[PDB]
Image (cartoon, rainbow over all chains, first blue to last red; front, side, top):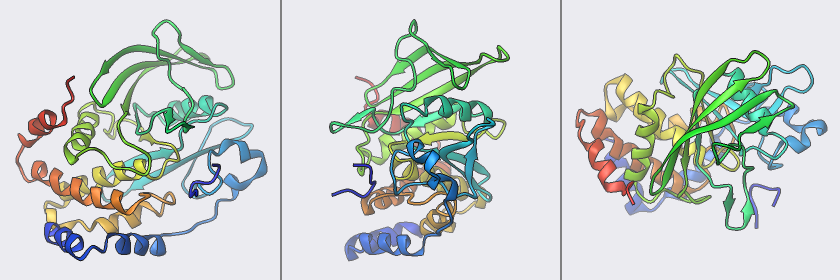
Length: 7
Length: 298
């Protein structure tokens, strides 16, 4: 997602 | 006694409360090098970076950046390197780090594929006869043997320095059943794995720090190093009641952000340090029960 905290 | 503290948190149910409390208290340092644009493609995640002050530095003249942190537990007397799962372009830097830092073991806690999302590049060879050659960093990597197990695999590798012809043996400890943001099947399977790593000598101080990695190098890798470090302190201090896991985790977080990713991973850490204390207290033979309990045969 490229972001470690995803949705 | 830490055993009491755990049963309180459970009955009370304040695990996420304790957890969020630690995010709030965790250190926060600059990450300038990680945020340089030339280094954009060397990071797997945009919100996970090494602090400038503990980042590992490649001994190459061009660009010395790799997303890896040196976690130097002064009291416990053990250093770890935590890093992200290598990217397709950083595999050569990974092994350059392993060589320059004189590591002897690598602990890998994730799988190359995990729920359809590629969380790591295939950076070690799977067949003896197809060895990898990293030309940018001048290293050759050969699989020599493996010992497959029901939930982990130990590989033996030869890392050759093409420049000097020198060679070294590297032990690869791959834990294959630990889901992202998840926890090991049991404290036993975990501790059996930890103690396998311990017995190999990879954690000895005659060697460079062991390299530990998962997808981002903070969540599962965090749980692993917290447990080993707490078990070390209980032994060095000579009292199991001594260790405050929250105080130890906060110490580690001075060296890399985000260690331990879920409230349930924090709980498993208490659980695992509580179980492992049996061994530290003198019950040498609980170790053989962990091996039995883990089903490492199948």
